[PDB]
Image (tube, rainbow, N blue to C red):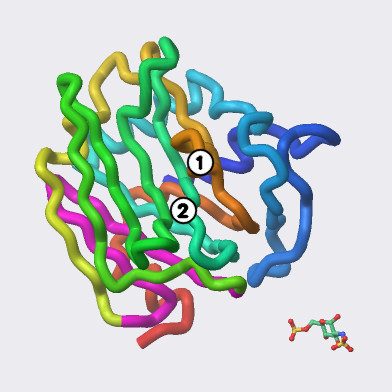
Amino acid sequence: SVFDIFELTGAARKGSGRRLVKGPDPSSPAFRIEDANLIPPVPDDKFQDLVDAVRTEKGFLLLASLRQMKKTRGTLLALERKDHSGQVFSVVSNGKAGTLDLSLTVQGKQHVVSVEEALLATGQWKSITLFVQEDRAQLYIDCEKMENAELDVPIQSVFTRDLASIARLRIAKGGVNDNFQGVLQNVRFVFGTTPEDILRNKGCS
Ligand SMILES: O=S(=O)(O)N[C@@H]1[C@@H](O)[C@H](O)[C@@H](COS(=O)(=O)O)O[C@@H]1O
């Protein structure tokens, strides 16, 4: 039901691309990104569980706590092709535009949609709940107004059957200048749950 990416990448060893620090959740590890390129990709087999879950739910619920450097574009997660030709999907906290950008590449064509009024790039802690189902995206920042956006294709369109054999899930690393600058905590894919339930359990209402 829950997929904690940092947990899936393995142990945060010395020279692993990240440094253990403190986060809003005191009973869970936080990681300051030092060199995203060094953070290992999620293992193929574990990513396959994610793909299958996404295909079944026709989407997903993505949770993330982030402390991002102001006015920077930071990739939260990305699915990079193994052949190095590019990314098939990515979620970027765009601090320059004040948006959360969702990029999907299907059949060679890249579609990018921005979730407006979403500035998460403040030197302080923010929490997001991203609910994507079909071609619909809903973003909740902490306990604020829900932000919405429509994708050009359904999300399962990206999560093809043999996706884990041609792509790999990377955390904090995206485009050339888009590696996440700051701290991340509890970046997770949650299934069989709704954003409504997670918001209450978080203390909102
Ligand atoms: O410099 S001090 O403020 O004296 N030191 C404070 C402590 O007093 C405080 O309990 C914790 C946690 O604080 S919390 O607000 O995040 O719970 O953070 C710092 O260590």
Which residue is drawn at the image coordinates 25% and 67% (left, top)? 116
Question: What's the magenta region?
Answer: 124-144
Q: Nearer the viewer, residue 125 or 114?
A: 114
Q: Nearer the viewer, residue 145 or 191?
A: 145
Q: Which mark is residue 73?
A: 2
Q: Are marks 1 and 2 in contact (CB under 8 Å)?
A: yes
**Crowd tier of the residue under label 2, counting other residues whose Cα lies within 10 Å: few below 14, some 14–19, many 20 or above:** many
Which residue is drawn at the image coordinates 13% and 40% (left, top)? 154
Total labels drawn: 2
Q: Which residue is mark 1?
A: 177
Q: Is residue 136 magenta?
A: yes
Q: Earlier in the sequence, mark 1 or mark 2?
A: 2
Q: Secondary structure at mark 2?
A: strand
Q: Which residue sits furthest bottom?
A: 205
Q: Is residue 128 magenta?
A: yes
The image position of residue 16, as x and y in percent, is 75, 33
Q: Which residue sits furthest right?
A: 14
Q: Nearer the viewer, residue 73 or 21?
A: 73
User: What's the residue type where badge 1 is placed?
Assistant: Asn
The image position of residue 8, as x and y in percent, is 59, 35
Q: Nearer the viewer, residue 165 or 104?
A: 104
**In the image, is residue 145 above or below residue 161?**
below
